[PDB]
Image (cartoon, helix red, strand yellow):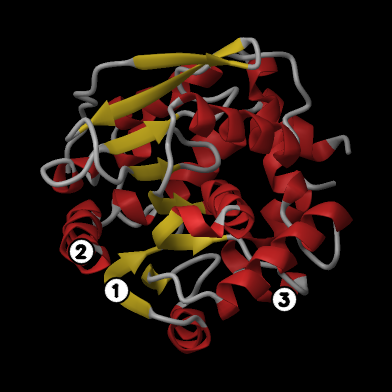
Amino acid sequence: IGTGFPFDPHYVEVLGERMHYVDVGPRDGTPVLFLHGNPTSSYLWRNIIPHVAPSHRCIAPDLIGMGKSDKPDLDYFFDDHVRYLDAFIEALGLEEVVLVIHDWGSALGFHWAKRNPERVKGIACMEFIRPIPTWDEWPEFARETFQAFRTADVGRELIIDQNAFIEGVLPKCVVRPLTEVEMDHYREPFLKPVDREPLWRFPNEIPIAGEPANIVALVEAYMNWLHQSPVPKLLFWGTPGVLIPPAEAARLAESLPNCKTVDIGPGLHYLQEDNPDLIGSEIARWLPGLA
């Protein structure tokens, strides 16, 4: 599994700030837009993009406050991310797109798709965000930690002071061991504690047992859209998974129209770090059927 990031940096200024993005493959045609989540960046897609770039333009932005993008002093609510990604997409002049999304990138991708359905040709997803009714549904190995992330005083000590989302959550949610050079790529944007605000606001925005209400409402809305939309869907899942365990992937294969599922083998949350080649090769095999 490759540890390098051989992509030339591209930057675009939107709403006063620069956003970094990978842009490879053909210069035109339908682009494939890769959206990462918490606490990652376009680095998470580095071994998947090479399977797709031979046929399609691949664009992978670093969300505002993350990766190589600038760091405005925001509270970094999901709504701030929505504003920046909406502006990024229009600044690049994108018309129709194929989405490849994960975690908070999936909440951004699905919410953008529900609002711009005529512009989405297909959605490839994995370990995505859905309304979580109770903590019972959260797996035991990670439940008490995520509860601490959402409690005062404690969640900020863990995520901002101790960097628990980078040093703990990230590697503990990859089955194979991440190496120090990979961990340093993920650590780079957050070397200064104050720059870790997005890492703490994100878990506090997850819709669980009804809160926060605004996010629950918007996630319910895109789920209803997804269950009634004929857009082609490709869902990758692992065992035991975290947000989408095996039993839930099988149920979604049924409850979502035109949905193909792919078993990646062992995996927790950052599936891209356990089987990037199967994820990339299957996306490449699936794209021509969208023509």
Residue 262 numbered mark, or none: 1
Residue 122, image quadrant: bottom left
Q: Which residue type does callout 2 highlight?
A: Glu
Q: How far apart are marks 1 and 3 (CA)?
A: 26 Å
Alpha carbon of mark 1 to alpha carbon of mark 2: how far? Answer: 8 Å
- Choose top left, top right, bottom left or bottom right for residue 6: top left
Q: Nearer the viewer, residue 91 or 172?
A: 91
Q: Are marks 1 and 3 in contact (CB under 8 Å)?
A: no
Q: Image check: 54 left or right of 170?
A: left
Q: Is residue 212 visible?
A: no
Kind of residue indicated by mark 3: Asp
Q: Which of marks 2 and 3 is nearer the N terminus?
A: 3
Q: Which amino acid does label 1 sit on?
A: Val
Q: In which quarter of the image is the C terminus?
A: bottom left
Secondary structure beneath label 1: strand
Is 188 positioned to the left or the right of 279 in the image? right
Residue at image point 72% right, 30% down: 76
User: Is the residue 258 above or below the residue 83 in the image?
Assistant: below
Q: Name the residue that disc number 2 marks.
A: 282
Q: Position of residue 55 (x, y in %)?
A: 14, 47
- Is the residue under label 2 in contact with that under label 1 (CB below 8 Å)? yes
- Marks 2 and 3, how far apart at CA: 33 Å
Q: Mark 3 points at which residue?
A: 136
Task: Tell us which disc is closer to us: 1 or 3.
Answer: 1
